[PDB]
Image (cartoon, rainbow, N blue to C red; front, side, top):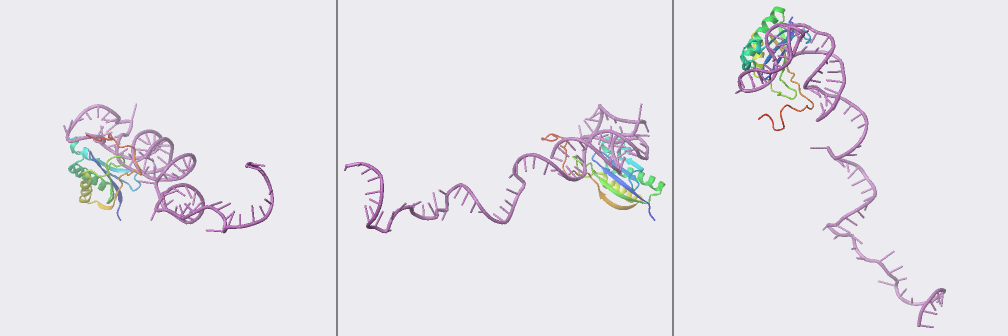
Length: 126
RNA sequence: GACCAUCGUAAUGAUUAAUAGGGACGGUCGGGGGCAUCAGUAUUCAAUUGUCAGAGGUGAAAUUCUUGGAUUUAUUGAAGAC
C-alpha cells in the first residue's frame, strides 16, 4: 500500500513554492519556497532554488510516511502569465529523484472565462 | 347660337411590364437592435482552515504586507465588471 499526498507546485517568475498536503488539501504536511533556500531576491525563482526546496519537502514527507504524491502544477494565471515559471520543472524532477512516487500530474493554472483589466496601460510596460 | 334629354354610328376608349423602383407572399439567414432572463471561470475581499518565514516586486534593488500568523493551501460566500 502507498500513502498519497498532493504536491502543489506554484511556479511564478519571482518564486517557486513546493507545497505538499493531504488529499483533502486542508492539512499542510510540508511547505518550502525557493526564497527559503537562497538569500538573493533575483534567484528565488531559479531552477537551483526550486531543487533545494523540493529535496527538503521530500525529506519531511518521508518522516511523516508519505510514499507517493499527486502533482498539481500552477502558474500565476488569472490576468497574469499562464506559462509556469523556470523552477516548476526542476521541483518536479527533484521530487522524483528524492524517491517519492509520482502519481497523476495536472495543470491547475487559473484561467478566466473573461478577465478583469490586466495591469499595465493600453500602451503596456515600456 | 348656346343648353338638357333620347335614339343612331364606332374595332367605341386603359402602351410595355425596364437584369428601374416600391409593395405583397414563401422558406430562411445573421456576434443587426431593444426589453426581460440564464450561466461561466477569474479578480479583490471577507468568514472557517491547516501550516511556518519570509511573501511582494525587478535588468538589479527599494517602497509594502508580515510569528496577532503574510504568501502558499482547502472550504463556503458576496460584490461589481468582463
